[PDB]
Image (cartoon, rainbow, N blue to C red):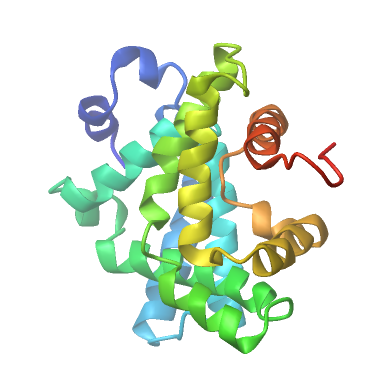
Length: 225
C-alpha cells in the first residue's frame, strides 16, 4: 500500500514504529504473494478448513505479528483500515471477504487441534461460539501490554479486572466446566499453534498467568506455580 494511506491511518509517532511504513522490498514481495495466494484460494472457492487455507492463514498471522511489531493496537488499526478505507482494494487487493477467509481459516487451524482434545459435545460448543467475542481480544491484549508496561500488580483490582475480562472471553468459547477448561490448558501446554496470532509476549503472558492464578486460586488444593 501507498504511504499516503498509512499516513492518514497512523499518527506520526506511530509511523516511527510501524514496519509497514518502512519501504522494504522483501516485505512488499511477501505480502504480494500472501494476498495473491489468498485471492487464488478464494477464486477456487477453497474451503477454510483445508490445509492450503490453514497454511496460508498461518503465514498471514506470522507476517502480521511481525509487521505490526507485536503491537495489538496496530493490528486493530489495520483491521479498521481494511474495512473502512475506500482505496483498500486498489492499493492492496485486500478485501473484507479475503480477511474473513483468512480469519476463519486460522480459526479452523485451532479447532482442528482442539478436535483432538475435546469430545464432540465440547467441540460443538467451541465451534459454535468461537466467533462470538473473537474481535474483543485485541483491545484486551493491548491493555495487558499496557498493564505490564506500567508494572501493574496482577493482584490489584485493576489487574484482577483484566483477568476477569480474559475469563469472559475464554469461557465464551471454552465453556464453564472446569473439566472442559483444563482440556484447553492441556492442549495449550502441548500445542504451540494454539498461542500463535495472539500478540502475546513472554512477559505479557507471564503477567496474565499471574493475574489468572490469583483469580482462580482455591483456598484448598494444589495452588498454581
